[PDB]
Image (cartoon, coloured by chain):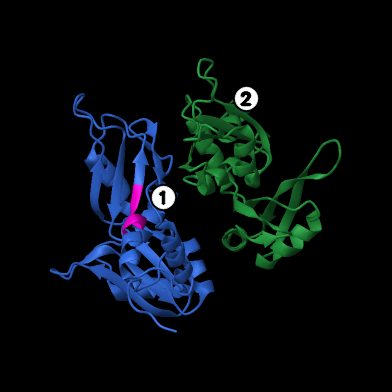
Chain colours: A green, B blue
């Protein structure tokens, strides 16, 4: 007797993985948005507004990520950033229709793990490389980069679980925006537990 | 050096305001004030106004006493739900050449291990604040802003640490720290301590 059927949990995770993006300059398109939001995790898809009479978007779009943590970082780091001369606005989807309690439950369950999300991981870095660097903040239980199911090549992001909460807190504070391999890592605390639907 | 005293003050003024949008029609100044006050006492609010329809236009500009309050509000109030709508928070779109000075100030700020602390309960004193925060490292100074007339602190202040690691640890540990009933709002300084003074070299 926990909270949220696997089906309810999956629906919440889906909503948690998308961010609303508004005030998009008329000349900007999907490719621009993608480039700007990709640093937080590879973009799964983008739903861009569109008007058939004017033949242009309506100034907003929904960017969907592969995991909730990417949307959380984009939310905290991309709001008010200037794109095409306008400060874009980023927010959570206004539609949640009763999903909020499940989302809250997931966030609560997440606190039971000292797990952090790391994005913008250079292609040449390996699991062991990431582990070594990050174990500088404390003992690590596991460090795993997400990988393409077909190629086996990592997708530029992963999760690291620490034995101690102090270690995870230190890592986030020190490694978010850390320049590694030419790009800047984006790092944040997990917003969901490791195997949410289990 | 970048910017004279006049240019610097103009930038500081812009840096102290945040645009607030998507405000539900039923909500007014009042509600915005209560929602944004945790980051520092509000100096004023410029609310949009239609008049023909006798309602506001859904946006407002909240002005704080210091740039650091606007910085925290920007990071913590965006997408917060108010009146059923997720409000939007951003920097003023008007900067007209002030950006380079704003950048200069941010660069100058990194030379100090200074942090901003807001939502400080009225009963806490400077030494109380110092004691709590010195748990992260040696402190050069801890000072709460005070009313020029009464001498009563305004619920916010700045702390300068000897070491950068100490300031970093403090922000990570004390932002949203429950103290005296309210939650502290803490962040790194975005301006150097006496921005319009001299300086030298």
Q: Which residue is drawn at 30% across and 45% down?
A: B61
- In the image, the segment drawn in magenta is B13-18
B170 vs B189, nearest the viewer:
B189
Residue depicted at x 31% and y 33%: B58
Quick check: B61 left or right of A37? left
Residue B115 seen in render: yes
Disc number placed over residue A150 in the picture, else none: none
Position of the N terminus of chain A, as image quadrant, is: top right
Residue with the mark numbered 2: A7
Query: Looking at the image, which is closer to me, B51 or A106?
Result: B51
Number of residues whose C-alpha sits closer than 10 Å to that of mark 2, classed few (under 14), some (14–19) or many (20 or more) = few
| Res B184 visible | no
Badge 2 element: helix
From this viewpoint, which residue is outermost toward the top? Answer: A53
Q: In this view, does B99 lie to the left or right of A2?
A: left
Residue at image x 59%, y 27%? Answer: A47
Q: Which of A69 and B12 is in front in this view?
A: B12
Query: Is disc 1 surrounded by few (<14), some (14 to 19) or many (20+) residues within 10 Å?
Result: many
Q: Name the residue under label 1.
A: B74
Q: Position of residue A90 (x, y in %)?
A: 49, 39
Q: Check the image and report above or below for B54 versus B186.
A: above
């Amino acid at each position: 007797m926990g909270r949220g059927s696997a089906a309810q949990r999956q629906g919440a995770l889906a909503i948690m993985s998308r961010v609303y993006v508004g005030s998009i300059y008329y000349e900007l398109g999907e490719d621009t948005i993608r480039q700007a939001f990709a640093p937080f995790g590879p973009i799964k898809s983008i739903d861009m507004s569109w008007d058939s009479v004017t033949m242009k978007h309506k100034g907003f779009a929904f960017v969907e990520y592969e995991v909730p943590e990417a949307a959380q970082l984009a939310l905290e780091q991309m709001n008010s950033v200037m794109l095409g001369g306008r400060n874009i606005k980023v927010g959570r989807p206004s539609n949640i229709g009763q999903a909020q309690p499940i989302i809250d439950q997931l966030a609560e369950e997440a606190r039971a793990f000292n797990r952090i999300y790391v994005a913008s991981v250079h292609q040449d870095l390996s699991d062991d490389d990431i582990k070594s660097v990050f174990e500088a903040f404390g003992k690590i239980k596991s460090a795993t980069l997400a990988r393409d199911p077909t190629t086996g090549k990592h997708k530029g992001y992963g999760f690291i679980e620490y034995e101690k909460a102090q270690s995870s807190q230190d890592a986030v504070s020190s490694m978010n925006l850390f320049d590694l391999g030419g790009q800047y890592l984006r790092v944040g605390k997990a917003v969901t537990p490791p195997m949410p639907l289990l």
